[PDB]
Length: 405
Length: 106
Ligand code: HEM
Ligand SMILES: *[C@@H]1CC(=O)N(CCCCCCN2C(=O)C[C@H](*)C2=O)C1=O
Ligand code: FES
Ligand SMILES: [Ca+2]
Image (cartoon, rainbow over all chains, first blue to last red; front, side, top):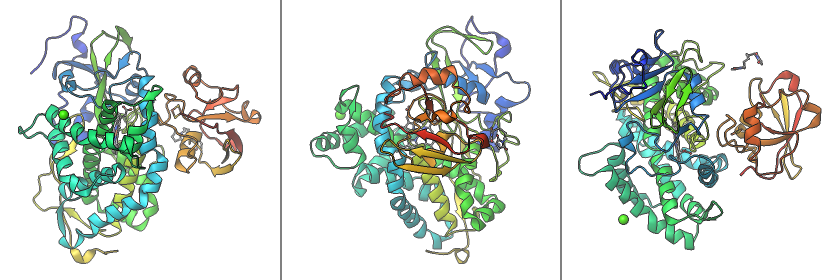
């Protein structure tokens, strides 16, 4: 399933890689991508698959490209481009200076000050999920914890009723993990229709929740429209589900396979924040890209207007040019560099909320269930895409080894 | 080493900042909210604006042309000692450096 080769592309840079089905995926999705980083692979390849696109395979180029939006535009940041159809969340596809307007507003609903005063409320949530899960000695972490936790946090900061959760879950599910029983465009529209009367109602009778703030904010020097507010509110929901769900699963998979790293955090919980950062580098998982605004020589390669380039957020921290022994998880690693939250003006708005969800999940899980492991006879499968993930995480443990608090 | 953060209202915070850490990173990690650091430290947003005290402007590496470009769109008063503090990487020689944090970043 390959596309014809563009007259401006030399064949010696051509490289067979499909980001939805990489070859050695059974070893681990991060491993599978790292094939782009073997010794005889140029810093910049072309692939004929998924429509046809460039790939930056190295942290230096990825960061450079993410730093130059004049050449590398967010107008089409998904590969293949058809995956952009009906994707109109805000501010994903905007560039400065308009993009900035929506980041100022967003910072008011998920900036560090908001994260901080939500923390204790987040840990009681985390605890409650864990506490009422412990004497089972088993779980599908992915369904049992990774999914309910972030969506429950959204409800908390959006000020939405708990029984609204089944509905939103379904809708975001159809978006992320389609069923054939609903198109993404339909699921998206349903989410907007859920949001839009709440927005209008709270524009005229405000609270302190995320929706009120966004609905009552200004962008470009005039009031945010209902349309703008739902498209951004929509992304504050969707932006922090599939990525938190999957990152927590990669991480939790690692700890279930590695008693030595558990005991370290168990003997030294003070290390957990630093370990989270290391877990973020090693199990990075986003890969999107940019589109070319113009013809452009780039690191000795000629790109043309319309060309899409993939700029894997995942690969920078795995680039051994950037971290020695990259597949190694060392919680005392001294110079951790990565682009797990992205890079440039679009670097993740939820980064502070997402770090705090990780650190609390770790501080609260190990506090109660120190020893656990992967289910016996368990084929744990990774999937590869824009947000790579874990299919399921059956965990097993002995109830007498835990400690309720 | 140690870095002192002076808010617009005169309030004064001194922080112990590890070598290799940017003045932005240290601010965000310790509840210095008047430093936002939106882009996370690549001179892409201008929300980590600070005024570096004249006693340390000889001692900080000059800004690169990228930082200069971004500084044009700071929202607070742009001054000669204006810096993106995500571009200030901390070192022992910079111990006790003074930065004044402006009344706005957004
Ligand atoms: C470990 C968890 C997460 C990871 C790895 C992650 C990853 C990313 C990345 C790499 C980007 C930049 C995309 C690009 O440049 O094309 C991004 C953008 C964004 N993220 Fe996250 N994310 C996480 C959690 C969250 C959470 C919890 C939220 C909560 C609202 C969130 C909200 C957003 C939003 C609203 C954007 C749009 C940023 C923009 O274009 O200005 N993310 N995310
Ligand atoms: C951690 C990652 C990084 O790039 N970095 C700065 C590079 C200098 C090498 C460390 C030398 N060093 C010290 O030992 C203290 C201050 C300093 O620059 C890091 O520090
Ligand atoms: S944090 Fe974005 S320019 Fe300093
Ligand atoms: Ca409708």
